[PDB]
Amino acid sequence: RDVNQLTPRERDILKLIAQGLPNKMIARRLDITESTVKVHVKHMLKKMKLKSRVEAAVWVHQERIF
Amino acid sequence: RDVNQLTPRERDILKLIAQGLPNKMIARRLDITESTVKVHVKHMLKKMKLKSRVEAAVWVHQERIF
DNA sequence: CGTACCCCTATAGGGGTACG
DNA sequence: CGTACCCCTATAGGGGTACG
């Protein structure tokens, strides 16, 4: 499970997720549609082999990735 | 925002959420139905003024509640 | 309090295609 | 890659009643 294997934008989303933001807020924050955010989210989840955004949030904090 | 304001069972749920577990898994781990888990989660969220289980997980880690 | 439902809407997520 | 949608099911959440 390596964070370097993610694309920049995927790391942008993971960071906002780890801060507790719902997809709609992440979209407004990055000024892109929720649709696009949701695409990055599932790509990130599959790559990192995580089952949900909460697991990604927890993982990011436990492993102090950011 | 104080963790002591929650009931014991609500802290039980909060801990499992901060470990990234979905409600169904929390029910099986605690040996209660998913319905009951959802009640505790709902109560916990309102009392702690959190908008989602993700904010609850992120809060627990940032403030090192547990 | 903790248990376990009911009702409903909102959010998330997993597959796909398409195109600068 | 990043964008933005399509499809769908799954999960989450907010209100309620009930009862030992």
Image (tube, coloured by chain):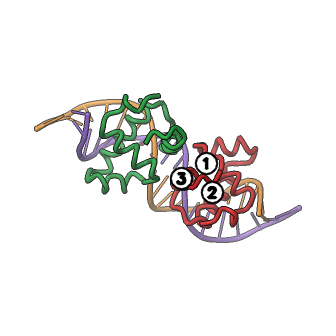
Chain colours: A red, B green, C purple, D orange
Q: Nearer the viewer, residue B33 or A35?
A: B33
Q: Tag on residue A5? A: none
- Identify the residue at image location x=49%, y=41%: B64
Q: Establish if B31 lies above or below C19.
A: above
> Which amino acid, mark 2?
Val
> Which amino acid, mark 3?
Gln
In what element is the residue under mark 2? helix
Label 2 vs 3, first from the N-terminus: 2
Q: Are marks 2 and 3 in contact (CB under 8 Å)?
A: no
- Identify the residue at image location x=39%, y=51%: B23
- The picture places residue A64, in percent across and down from the top left corner, at 60, 52
Front tag of 2 and 3: 3
- Identify the residue at image location x=51%, y=61%: A51
Q: Tag on residue A17? A: 1
- The picture places residue A8, in percent across and down from the top left corner, at 75, 58
Provide the chain ID for the residue under circle 3.
A
Label 3 vs 1, first from the N-terminus: 1
In what element is the residue under mark 3? helix
In what element is the residue under mark 1? helix
Q: Establish if A47 lies above or below A22.
A: below
The residue under label 2 is: A41
Q: Tag on residue A62? A: 3
- The picture places residue D9, in percent across and down from the top left corner, at 46, 62
Provide the chain ID for the residue under circle 2.
A
> What crowding class fits label 1: few (fewer than 14 Cα within 10 Å), some (14-19), or many (20 or more)?
many
**Quarter of the rendering occupied by the C terminus of chain B:** top left
Q: Are marks 2 and 1 in contact (CB under 8 Å)?
A: yes
